[PDB]
Structures are given as structure tokens and as C-alpha cells.
Amino acid sequence: ANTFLEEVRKGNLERECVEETCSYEEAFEALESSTATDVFWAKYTACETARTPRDKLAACLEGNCAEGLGTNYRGHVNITRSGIECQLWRSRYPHKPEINSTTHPGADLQENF
Amino acid sequence: DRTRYFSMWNQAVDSYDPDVRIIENHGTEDELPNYCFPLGGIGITDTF
Ligand SMILES: [Ca+2]
Ligand SMILES: [Ca+2]
Ligand SMILES: [Ca+2]
Ligand SMILES: [Ca+2]
Ligand SMILES: [Ca+2]
Ligand SMILES: [Ca+2]
């Protein structure tokens, strides 16, 4: 955002929307891949507490750790705290989830992760 | 005469500049700004 003459130089997704509080416009401009754009947005949002420092935002981009209540987690662990198998979020077996893939598509709902 | 130069005996007087021995200072007319623009014509630009 700062260093006004940045909009004439080429840019770095990391030298605009990472090491600096950025516009989703410059984010949109730099991303275009609107799926990953939503991903980066989701990042930003969850990383709202990971805005600083820089390496914290880098880790929040890695996504292996759940931020706060766990909106950002994108790992491969699909097991409950006590070893019970996780039911498919979209499937109705054995429970029909009021809160499921249709209601939360932006969390990247995997098989049972 | 002595102003004129003859190029045979190197006959050419040596005189200073009358505006350097005495500096008649007057400032400089600069009522208008002299700006310098971008090369393309527009700098910053957005998207629409
Ligand atoms: Ca900037
Ligand atoms: Ca900027
Ligand atoms: Ca900078
Ligand atoms: Ca731009
Ligand atoms: Ca930019
Ligand atoms: Ca950097």
C-alpha cells in the first residue's frame, strides 16, 4: 500500500499482500486465479491474527496449523481426538449435517479431514 | 582600430567580459511553473 510509486513497478504478492497491509484489489490484481484468490482471502481473514510478523503470515500460508478456532487448517488429519473415524462432511451417513459442504464451501472440505 | 583581429602577427587584444568584472544582478523571471511530465502521458492508472 505504502511507497506510492509501487503501482508502476512490477509487484510481489509477498511485497504487497504479505510484508504490507494490502488491498484485496492489489490482491485481486495479482491473483486473478479467483479460486486461489478466495484461498488467499481466506488466508488473510484467518491470518487476521497472523498479519504480523512476516514469517507468521508465511506459516499461515502453509496452513498446517489451525488459527484460533481452526478456520484455516488445511492438513491431512482426518481423525477425531479419540481415534473415531471422521464422517464425510457432505454425506448424510450417519447424520445429515445442517453445517456441511453446501454451507461451508470455502473451508476446502476434503474427504474427512 | 584595435577591436578587429589580424591573423598574421597574432594581433588580437585581450579583454575580459564586461558582465563578469561587474555583476549586474537582476534575478530571473519565473512567474510560471515549468513542469515535467510522464513519458506516456498518464502515470498512475487503475483498471475498470
Ligand atoms: Ca505498497
Ligand atoms: Ca500498494
Ligand atoms: Ca517497500
Ligand atoms: Ca495495481
Ligand atoms: Ca501492485
Ligand atoms: Ca520480501
Image (spheres, coloured by chain):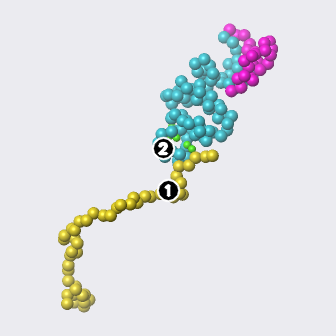
Chain colours: A cyan, B yellow
- Is mark 2 in CB contact (under 8 Å) with mark 1? no
Q: Which residues are magenta?
A: A82-106
Q: Is residue B46 visible?
A: yes
What residue does disc 1 label? Answer: B38
Q: Position of residue A12 (x, y in %)?
A: 55, 41
Looking at the picture, which amino acid does disc 2 mark? Phe
- For the residue with label 2, is its CB less than 8 Å from the closest atom of ligand 2? yes
Placement of A83 over or under A38, stated as above or below: above
How crowded pointer 1 is (Cα within 10 Å; few <14, some 14-19, many 20+) is rated as: few
> Mark 2 highlights which residue?
A4
Q: Which residue occupies the foreground of this view, A9 or B7?
A: A9
Kind of residue at disc 1: Pro
Is A99 left, or right, of A52 in this rendering? Answer: right
Task: Specify the quadrant of the image occupied by residue A87.
Answer: top right
Q: Which chain is disc 1 placed on?
A: B
Residue A19 in the image, given as x and y percentages of width and height: 51, 34
State the SS at label 1.
loop
A12, above or below A54, in the image:
below
Numbered tag placed on residue A87 in the rendering:
none
* Residue A35 inside the magenta-drawn segment: no
In the rendered image, which quarter is residue B29 located in? bottom left
